[PDB]
Length: 289
Ligand SMILES: O=C(c1ccc2nc(C3CCCCC3)oc2c1)N1CC(N2CCN(c3ncccn3)CC2)C1
Image (cartoon, rainbow, N blue to C red; front, side):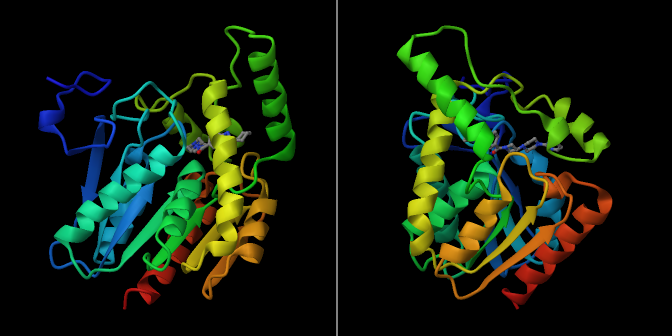
């Protein structure tokens, strides 16, 4: 019996098998009646789909069918943890899931919501299907990395590759600098489905590939979007938010900057998180009326 990394049989769980034969754990939040639209939620590196429960419940309350999976190497899905052969695998697997849901609900508009790496995945998914998605909501998407961090990582990756240095990775995710809400930090840290290990050089290289590919995709993007960004984001530099506003060709694009807020806006201080939920609710409501 194929089992999750936590030893639970997939036969008992919602799942999909991707093109590489790997089982991905799925999550669904369906309203009681006919949905007005579909929305795929794309989580970031080191986390998983269960971290979106409250956002998904809000969106389902707007009569959308919300759906997600754990990206390969994450959460309850198969794969070596926080490894991917090529970043495109994530996008391919999103497109499989979206295509399979759309055929079950033909004619319904489909939105994307993504955070951080999951925002880069959203951008690249929309760009691979020009004109197809109804909208995207991006919470601190990975567009430009913090320049000092990116340089540090490139130097590390070069040392590791050009001197074959062993047992060296980049640092782990530091949740304490990614939200001001200490309670949320503690909740995240004790989640059994996150990855707390150092980021491997091979995965970092794929995140740099994502950044490069995002920049090439931006001038091609036409999908409507809402972009939410914290000014004190230590991971996804706010300069990237401005680059997305500048280069996307979308006729419907809006940016809200949260002054002083850190990266994880949907798990931030209550004044910020409450606003984030409100803004997403209004923006999606207006576009599914
Ligand atoms: O997608 C990411 C992520 C993680 C690590 C990264 N490193 C880079 C750069 C580094 C330089 C080279 C180019 C790539 O980009 C990343 C993106 N995620 C999702 C985010 N996490 C943070 C922790 N979280 C959290 N923290 C506190 C409270 C609640 N949740 C959940 C979401 C981080």
